Image (cartoon, grey):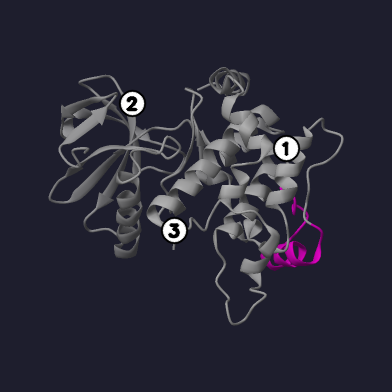
């Protein structure tokens, strides 16, 4: 069992450590200053993310950080969920040391300014489905907020579900029909199928480089399109495999009673393919970052 405070376990090795052992390399991402830091563990050279939860901080927020951390700590055996290396507890702060990902899919799309290849999305789909399934099966957690910002990638070619909100209960953009409008009054609660829909939308957005409801000027207009319009499917003339089109058509079934749960999606040929097909996500990632690098 991982040493949950005063230690960092990284690689397979446990290191006694404390906050002064980390060099602060600044905000982990744009406007993350004061709260999530990129830091270098001086003893090993590892560069990690450190979330700083101030004791004086917002209480609801700290409650969510703690719930999410509880789930991350008990998700040590899931390869598809970002890992906690350890924590440091001082009189004024908790520092939560996390795996450092390069970017989320939302920032990746913004930086790319175009379609993300099918092969990359195949590996992504496998990782995220397996992460969501693990969460529900092991921890009883319905994620409730699947979208590109919660899908993380790195230069090692790993693709993992973000810790943010990973404990479950704008991005109304990704809301399933039945979540917008529970078709049964007497049994109103959406379930994991609503996250399936969100995954489908996310895939189409990433595959095309266009959010499927882009021409909407208000959040409510987007909800009206989700309900009134045919599900926004993959185009037929971008060379997408029939497996990918099917996978997405399945995820985007409007009638949630006919939409696959994770168990069923894990049988899909799209997933079976990308479980075993070798895809060099690492090289791809490094290449596209290099091609889109702005001078310092």
Please say if the residues under marks 3 and 1 sit with CB atoms less than 8 Å apart: no
Mark 3 and mark 1 lie on one chain; the one further toward the N terminus is 3
Give the alpha-carbon distance from disc 2 to disc 3, as whole Å.
28 Å
Q: What element carries label 1?
A: helix
Mark 2 and mark 1 lie on one chain; the one further toward the N terminus is 2
Give the alpha-carbon distance from disc 3 to disc 1, as whole Å.
28 Å
Q: Which mark is residue 244?
A: 1
Q: Is residue 212 magenta?
A: yes
User: From which residue to which does the magenta span run?
Assistant: 211-230
Give the alpha-carbon distance from disc 2 to disc 1, as whole Å.
35 Å
**Mark 2 or mark 1, which is nearer to you?**
1
Q: Is mark 3 on a helix, strand or loop?
A: loop
Mark 2 and mark 3 lie on one chain; the one further toward the N terminus is 2
Please say if the residues under marks 2 and 3 sit with CB atoms less than 8 Å apart: no
The spot of residue 138 in percent (x, y) is 39, 51
Q: Which mark is residue 168?
A: 3
Q: What element carries label 2?
A: strand
The quadrant holding residue 221 is bottom right
**Mark 3 or mark 1, which is nearer to you?**
1
Judged left or right of residue 104, residue 98 is left
Judged left or right of residue 216, residue 178 is left
Q: Can residue 34 be seen in this view?
A: no
The spot of residue 66 in percent (x, y) is 29, 55
Picture layout, residue 71 above or below residue 190: above
Q: Which mark is residue 47?
A: 2
The spot of residue 180 in percent (x, y) is 64, 69
Picture layout, residue 268 above or below residue 254: above
Picture layout, residue 142 above or below residue 209: below
């Amino acid at each position: 069992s991982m040493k949950q405070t005063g230690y960092l376990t990284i690689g397979g090795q446990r290191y006694q450590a404390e906050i002064n052992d980390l060099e602060n390399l600044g905000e982990m991402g744009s406007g993350t200053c004061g709260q999530v830091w990129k830091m270098r563990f001086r003893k090993t050279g590892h560069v990690i993310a450190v979330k700083q939860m101030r004791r004086s901080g917002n209480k609801e927020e700290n409650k969510r950080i703690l719930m999410d951390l509880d789930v991350v700590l008990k998700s040590h055996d899931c390869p598809y969920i970002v890992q906690c290396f350890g924590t440091f507890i001082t009189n004024t702060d908790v520092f939560i040391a996390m795996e450092l990902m390069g970017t989320c899919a939302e920032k990746l799309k913004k930086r790319m300014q175009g379609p993300i290849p099918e092969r990359i999305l195949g590996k992504m789909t496998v990782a995220i489905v397996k992460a969501l399934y693990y969460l529900k099966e092991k921890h009883g957690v319905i994620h409730r907020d699947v979208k590109p910002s919660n899908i993380l990638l790195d230069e090692r070619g790993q693709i993992k579900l973000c810790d943010f909100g990973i404990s479950g209960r704008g991005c109304a953009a990704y809301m399933a029909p039945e979540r917008i409008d529970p078709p049964d009054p007497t049994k109103p609660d959406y379930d994991i199928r609503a996250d399936v829909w969100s995954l489908g939308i996310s895939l189409v957005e990433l595959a095309t480089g266009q959010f499927p409801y882009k021409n909407c000027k208000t959040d409510f207009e987007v909800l009206t399109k989700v309900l009134q319009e045919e599900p926004p499917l993959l185009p037929g003339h971008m060379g997408f495999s029939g497996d990918f089109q099917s996978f997405v058509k399945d995820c985007l079934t409007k009638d949630h009673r006919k939409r696959p749960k994770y168990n069923k999606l894990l049988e899909h040929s799209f997933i079976k393919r990308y479980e075993t097909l070798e895809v060099d996500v690492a090289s791809w990632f490094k290449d596209v970052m290099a091609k889109t690098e702005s001078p310092r």
